[PDB]
Length: 341
DNA sequence: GGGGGAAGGATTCC
DNA sequence: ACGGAATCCTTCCCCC
Ligand SMILES: Nc1ccn([C@H]2CC[C@@H](COP(=O)(O)OP(=O)(O)OP(=O)(O)O)O2)c(=O)n1
Ligand SMILES: [Ca+2]
Ligand SMILES: [Ca+2]
Ligand SMILES: [Ca+2]
Ligand SMILES: [Ca+2]
Image (cartoon, rainbow, N blue to C red):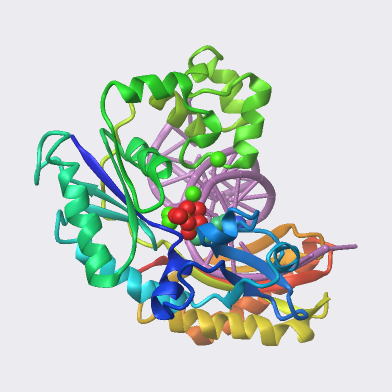
């Protein structure tokens, strides 16, 4: 089995540089403004020009401007990136319809069939890395190896606009040297917790007692890692479908006033149905970020699809439910629809 | 003891 | 106490 991973480089930002080529070479920073007050928001993604000066995804738009006050700060236009993504996906979709669109800018391509060998598989990378650059002028890094997890690791190592192959030997070198913190799906929180238990390499997960792990990071997350250190991972490249769609918005001011919130909540839903588009959801989650940034949410699953009229109706109840089991004032409020029909 | 699921909390950027 | 979209995942639950 041979898996080929593709990752669009600084995607949201690069897309913008493609829509306005006057930025290429300039620090471009795609942001998300909450409108709570000018420059209130966070950085979604930056290009390498911004990044090399300390501007990364997640920091407040304010602190980002203190570093690079003269960079091009642009608002998020997910929709645009979405269509661009689709096109690139269908583009890839023609090298193995046994692909997995992991995210708006990640995709795992099973090239087991289409080509056997680490030489011809690599040359399928440029055959693809060149076409995407040609057909849509987008630079995409390629990762290639035995399973999704290492192909993914390969790309993170070669970026941007690069390519790398992690054969069966390297996989072995990494499991003993790769920083646990660099493993796909291991966030800051999970990495830290691993420092404690005494883990810093994928291999260390073999010393500790499964039971200890299972308690600090969970069975699943636990099995995942052990599985990796054993080169005994292998998980198929499968279709995968967005399993939820939603919208959370920051209210102009905080509150605990049901009637002051409604409009935002009702805007979240209406704006969530547009993005649903025909798909029918049977589960709804009214979500609310607290005054202290804690995500509290209450949902409900029905034995049928949820008509929008019903969303309005139920979204309120769930909201009234929240206010009951909490104290904090609500800052951001939104909805989430799932369990599609 | 454990299936099948809903619900709520937590974490990754998938 | 500066944003947002999703998913992961650990517990509660009805009941065989
Ligand atoms: N705090 C964060 C961190 C990340 N993201 C988004 C940014 C786009 C998406 C994927 O990010 P990466 O995989 O890190 O890629 P990138 O940042 O878009 O750029 P590159 O692929 O070149 O690393 O996650 C976000 O919204 N909020
Ligand atoms: Ca990317
Ligand atoms: Ca990515
Ligand atoms: Ca990490
Ligand atoms: Ca990443």
